[PDB]
Length: 144
Length: 149
Image: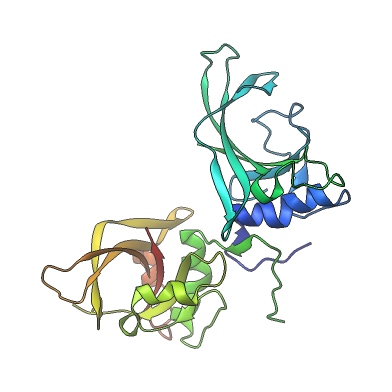
């Protein structure tokens, strides 16, 4: 348990997410943190307040374009992914996805948004050692 | 213990009402209030472009206790000019304060040069909140958040 003074909360920069949460989850198989739980993507749905937080945003690890669709909708990738720089080095990429209610290609537009952080640049699959599972991503999900 | 070791990514990120409730009120109660999150400096003595040089890593905004002015938003090398409409701050069904936005301009008060340095000044307010202070309190303080567009 962590005893936060008032006003202090979990509000990470991108490079903080990579460097101190995602690279460890990849490099070390036994990794845990107090602010980022583990959830399987396909199981839950964007209307799942109890699973995993604070400031109306929810972070977690994910084990795995509309390449992932929900029992009740899908996630559509939107926009040019932002690059994550640790100073002069590239370290990761942030994809932005939006959740669509109706499963049809013209599906109902919900206000649920996800940021998917992945390892890149210096931590691309080629540079990554084989003692690593590049299958892990970080997702931040929020509304509107 | 004031050590407050913070895991990565945890940082001061108050809501407007948390600023009022846990930081401004205590300062106007006791002038000798201090908190690690908020410095105490005279906005007059500091030019904002100096701030990113003393920035710790990932630090993008700065909070300060300052004194209230009376008709002066003035800086040796510049000046702050308000903009837009002040914004109400609530605790439940009560107004407890307001937040004003200001923009920084070049030293010359006529025809200054607009900067991308923005300020949010936070002040107590609300008829009943301000009316029910103990006579031992002094409402001569505001909280300034300084940051860059």
